[PDB]
Image (cartoon, rainbow over all chains, first blue to last red; front, top):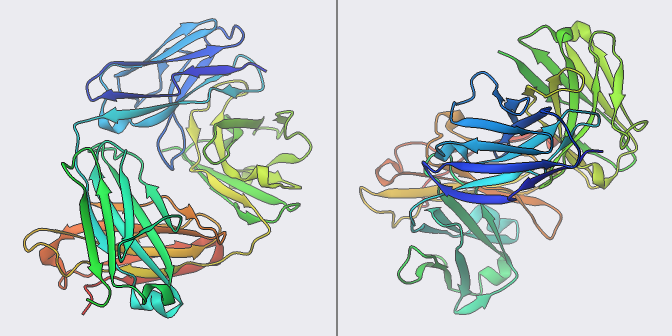
Length: 213
Length: 220
């Protein structure tokens, strides 16, 4: 088969930057190369065919170049909605083969998270389990640390985090940390605290509640 | 406009089969062939083959030849992919994508998730993430729904039957040590709206035929 190799695997660039990603074919494929844009949870969208021609509807800031084995895709002026994984593909010969994709992230100014904590509902407590949720909303960069304490005992191994994909409009992230305990354990303790560390915060922000208040 | 709608995916046991359908509209079905492409979670795109829609002649990637087959119902403008003797490694999002033989694929279906597992389907419990009583007067408040303990993916979540979209974050599900998924969907709103505006998260877990509307309000 023909292998398609893309570089870099990921890149970060600011709005308005000119950005170029590359695709190398293991054999001559003429100009029989297409590029696709895939946004989170969506189907790939066709951008370019025969290495350099735009599908109709595709914004003019997208372009492609190359022939033989070396191909490029360029975004002349990166926009927040261009956050996506970009794939090259050859159709010189079957089987059709794709590169592993290049993940393009938007670089923006630092934005501190807004933090919220949610106690377990009484409904859930009836089922024998308590989930405590800490929300970090609309922050940048993605790196954040969340620390759980229950009556000043550090909680390790009983929380899971999930992060949203970068927002297509403001280029921020949001993050949930969910602490799970038994009902019995939940009711043995008073102070539930979520401590957040992030570049946009001069010192860690703690949100907390006392059970029953 | 050109539309490709996939169905027939979802949960299937190892050793089992599914038959995916790709229903086309907005163009003359037999004027273009159809490709099938899959994408395992977190991985790249893998072309599985192409079918000639005018006479029904399929071409397969060597990796799936024999075990997967393509067929048509032109009267329904529909292409099918029957996938057999499945294994965990076949768990992926499956796409149909319109196109000529040996050429680019200019329109893709939305994709359907196939989960190969011997575990049973399980619908989610939906719990409120109640807005804080300490929410800032004249400020912004957060609330949400915890959608817990379901299998397999996916679930959809909307707010107020789709009327509320601004400020919504529905988090990627996480697999719990129980083998069940869980996620939260949250939204930020004006603090002043709490107790006046109704906030309902609409949850639909198709594999278990579980639809739940959960109202989220301040706790008393």
